Amino acid sequence: GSSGSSGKIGYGKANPTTRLWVGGLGPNTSLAALAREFDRFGSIRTIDHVKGDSFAYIQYESLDAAQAACAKMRGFPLGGPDRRLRVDFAKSGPSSG
Image 1 (tube, helix red, strand yellow):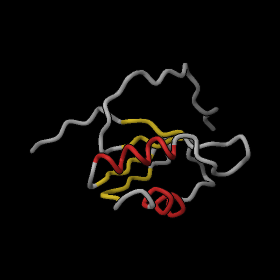
Image 2 (tube, helix red, strand yellow; image 1 turned 120 degrees about the vertical axis):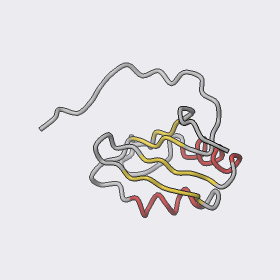
Image 3 (cartoon, helix red, strand yellow; image 1 turned 90 degrees about the vertical axis):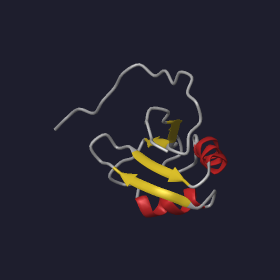
Image 4 (cartoon, one colour; image 1 turned 60 degrees about the vertical axis):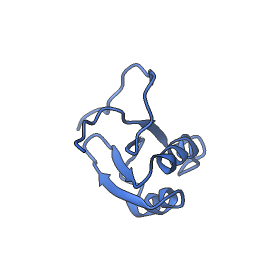
């Protein structure tokens, strides 16, 4: 099937938000496993598992916690030796309050 998806890396500036964009996921990585690794940071508000694009969205009751995981996880040792997790700040996302 599809031959994967490749482009031109470039994680420009992005304001910190409770929401976090997690990628580099595959048919091997198990949500549960992560849910625990991420939780270690702070009480996870919400979680989202998507195979299509292989992205995961995890909300945090507090912003601080979100950031901690974002950076900490950023390039976390999970799976192969040269295989690391890719996390970024998902600014895009309008909300009402």
